[PDB]
Length: 274
Ligand SMILES: [Zn+2]
Image (cartoon, rainbow, N blue to C red; front, side):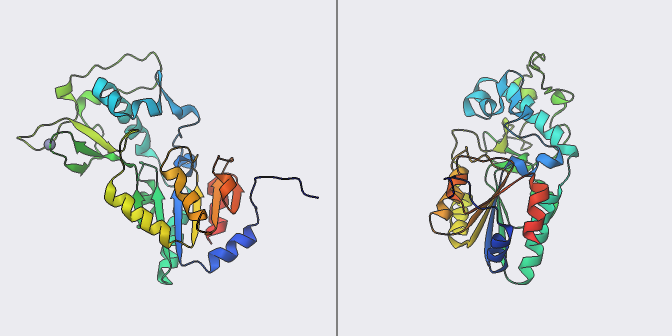
């Protein structure tokens, strides 16, 4: 007899049968998908920046309290992201999307990442549900612009260093990134969702619908801790739709899915998307 496990199947063959006949694939992604591009995640070494956990600084009170510190933090991340490049897991998702579109089959990417590496990969049908490290939003007027400038403002040049006893830059509020609209000159915030802030209503509305129409769901490189994203694949599996996790470890959501493929997703995902 089998001893009870809450580890789903690892049978690639059985998954690839579902993949062969699937018309609307929803692929959900977290930081794990960029791990092999050399971009740190929230669990390992990159969970910490100076004396804070990354989640501590991605908060409205943090910005309210020390806008300069929070801008240092996001400036560090923008600069780290700059060099990095799509790994074979990103590109396989783009290729899969390309190929299957010609046969009228849809592949939608719903990413928690704010690194735009799916866009740089060639993926086209993408919801960035937590915004983007390379967009600004104005605190007064609300303009969302892309912004890939190194550095976003001269005052941040050479700053944002991660070490815990690094000297604070204490940039005055007027010398932080400012809205380029003359006659507003408001303080910019990065255009990302912070813990305690609602996701964009139209994006989420659209994502719910994509999830309702999907007949197969992939969940790659996410810890499934941050809600609401964490409950997406769970809700799909609540409709009897097969879900397959691609992760180095188990998550508290793995239990609810049909398949689970342990390992670095740059290796496990491309053979599953062929
Ligand atoms: Zn403005």
